[PDB]
Length: 123
Length: 123
Image 1 (spheres, one colour):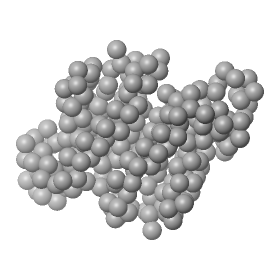
Image 2 (cartoon, one colour):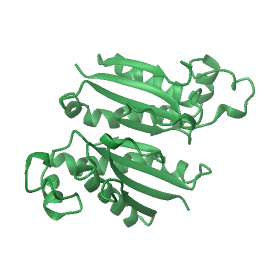
Image 3 (cartoon, each protein chain N blue to C red):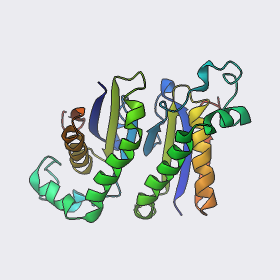
């Protein structure tokens, strides 16, 4: 079956070369100036809470998975092993990490074959 | 005002480094095996007609502009000069060219500041 890859990255490091879709989340609320959140990542509960208190964050996740679901039946049959969705913020530590996690969890919940990767955190 | 750039490219040449959003259209009907269409581009009427006879082509354009419109108000105010939407097929000659053109025409019709670019055709 098609493997759905959800990856976060920082635009400052360049777009990942395996991406098929790229979504920029630099318009979402930015935790960069709260000093307590700066050293954390979007895997951490305070950063997730900072993001989820804003309505547009859940709406971005919901609308993005809905958009992808329009094409998924045709992609699952596109001579294709992978569908790679890359979520980018500037540094790849906070917003993109959280959003990629939430998308990956949503598609896992739908029974899809999924994998996540955080390009900045893995360094 | 925010300048909306719509660019086509071929994944075989790599993702353009100025892209903010990237949409893969390799699942749309492929004119590669009709020999009359192969040397043409998505600027040409026979290629546009080949694509537009399939319902999913118009739906992709409509759904993609609608998705972008969810975020445009927040992007038009993201300390941002450009919003660059890159549409990719394998070679960047047919599907991506057509789709980028149609998106650019749609946002021009809404009074947005727009520019188009076809990375493969310009070579």
